[PDB]
View 1: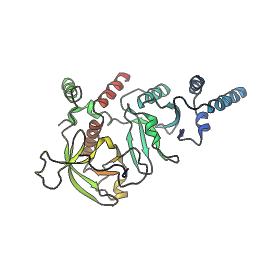
View 2: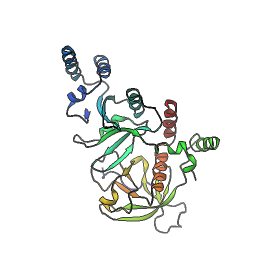
View 3: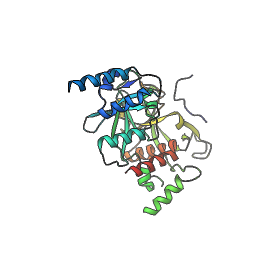
View 4: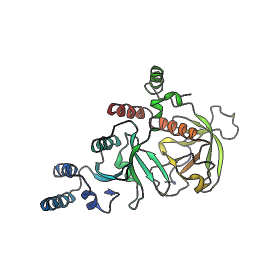
Length: 306
């Protein structure tokens, strides 16, 4: 019932040289906002140099991180992020700084350059929590960009649960109820074998708790199917260049990985779809499954800011 293991059996700045460079990278109002919290022309260059040193003598309390966020146009922004802040808050901060259009597609996006995987942050996720799993010498980056797939189901619920008013009923039925209705989603995918550049086609089914399969005949798709993986154990990511790197049949790949793992590992599960549409279906479906009603709330909170 538990399925495959996603783990083997039983930092203060991210994107900067040291705590100094990160604080030197803060905007004016932000540096002053930190000073306000921390306590309880040539003169500017020296006064803000002392604010730095004063601030650098400030530990305990609500723990803080300075996070470099990478923008569309290759610029960056350094944000103060304490451990109570969700992606929703960091987003709200980025909407103020950038004066963007505040559409629902804007999101934080993590990239793992070594593992070549990437995913949206969900808006309810604790930013510090996510970044804590990263190593000291990490290549990982946080991006601010538009991903119009992130709330696909809420814009077009008919495209996943296989008119303005009917969409409403579908979502209310699917989300605004006693329990979440996960899309009826089943099909063949290619599962990468542990530690090998080889892939096997298996028939898989989406359930609220995880991905399930038909073991070996066992009455085909009956109701005594086995558990491949539970969603509580993993985040879902896009896999990049799985074709070239692992001989994946296609480049339409998702990756299921425990947050903690930061290196090539056989506990990381790679799945390959036949086309881009099947990938889209599975990613949205697994996200609906894992996050349920929270995802719907995330959507509603975003539409309010639009």
